[PDB]
Length: 6
Length: 221
Length: 210
Ligand SMILES: [Cl-]
Image 1 (cartoon, protein in one colour):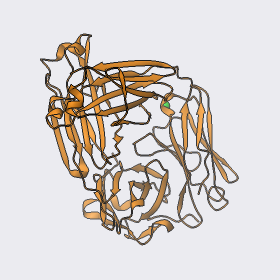
Image 2 (spheres, protein in one colour; image 1 turned 180 degrees about the vertical axis):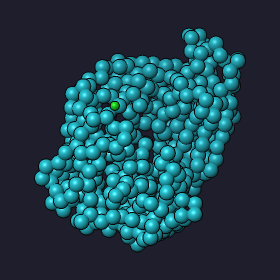
Image 3 (tube, chains in turn purple, brown, orange; image 1 turned 180 degrees about the horizontal axis):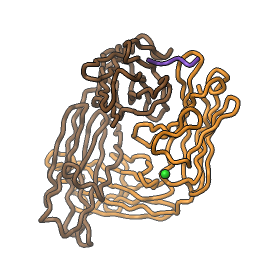
Image 4 (cartoon, rainbow over the protein chains, first blue to last red; image 1 turned 90 degrees about the vertical axis):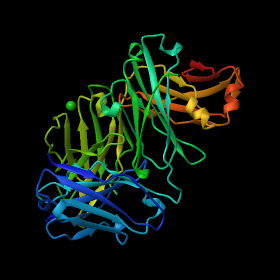
């Protein structure tokens, strides 16, 4: 669920 | 090693713009995101947002939309923060901070920070005065010599002795802010009283906001 | 947005624990809580990530955990170098990062130490520019409270006096500086100028003369 900043 | 090196401190007037660079070395720049963090003097860290080095897309924190632009020049492995329409409350140290894999919400490497001072007041480079020890003052084994860095604006100043070769016994003191609005600071190094007459001592005073560096030789009284 | 107590304290060798309270939408929702240590005027340094993990070079003296909506950093075996500000951070369900306000950790037990005082007279060069300044440098005192008085000959002086507030040194002792601005005739017209630093009722005095 945690968005990948890249 | 992984390293983030930021541009020098700057003074800017209200409504002006400023661009701070964060040059990455030691890893594949486009492989990891870059975050920006602000720290107002005496205050805490605030996250400003992040930029993807793969797409170039920026994402801004709610408090930092509109006047803040994250950008990149990948050909020189550099991330840029531009602040437009500068306000008094923008005065802060800005850090670039790399996003650790796999998602980038941990900051493993940080730039050294850049002090942006927003003020209408004019820049003023320091006047540097060498402080020689009196003969009586060298009567004990050691002597304390120094440099007065007087009437500058804005922060910061860095002081070294003999281009960084002499660091032991060096005490550089935090600046005083005078009613006039200008800063002054002092740096002192204690040396053997036997070495005056033989060893040369030079204070190097750097004031990047005015891009001025002075080296004074502390001579005899 | 994350709530940390403003300070923390412990004696050398003992433990300190610092709390960081968020919500179910950050600390309580995810495992991306970080702790950063910051010495004055230096960049923050990662010491804990993903709630309990340590980056390369950080000893296990530093540990992190969380329960419910509150994360906690424990520094065991406290040493003087641990004196610093500590910031927590967490990911949010809004895909943002939030910081705590920071906790200043002080290491206690340091003994009383009197100030060392160096006092410089105005230089020839400064005088030449009609800009004499007496420089009084105060260092290595503890606790971090001092009062400074300036004396012209035998009488008090208070105009053109600038004194910093004490700041922590890199050895957790304290330093300050005081400046007496004069004019060249103010300077030469007296017999001696003095800087007197009082600390816990006791005074260290320095005097210079033209
Ligand atoms: Cl250690």
